[PDB]
Length: 141
Image 1 (tube, rainbow, N blue to C red):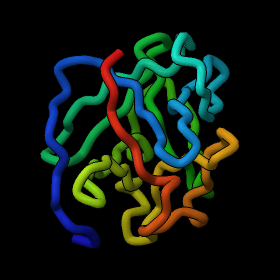
Image 2: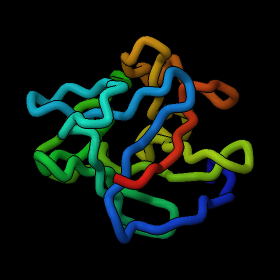
Image 3: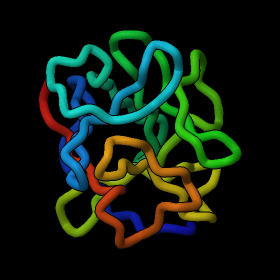
Image 4: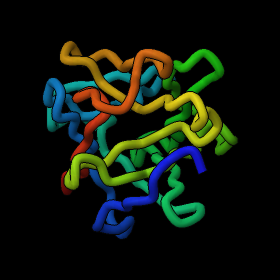
């Protein structure tokens, strides 16, 4: 293991909005496969269904389009039509409150899912423990 194992509470029974405490944006997987953030709660591409593959390992899927959140070899988030190794994330509790998502494939490099204050996603190498960009709160839809 390259990381701790404090897990967040809550389950995967229903879809969620992944709210980023940094700028207040909700993670969005666009129909064209791009990933960013939006403050518009009415957006139809921010409803995400998480599922557990192994304890603490999850897929994050758009309920609207079926795409899986994934992080590519250069650290960019994208929407994948099919589940692959780039789609698995280590879901952990952070600062005794938030959920963080580390790329399983790049776990040794500490690459996280993160949103900047302007709504753009962070590239894996630019994320790290301690940032506000990596902190999320799963809100009901």
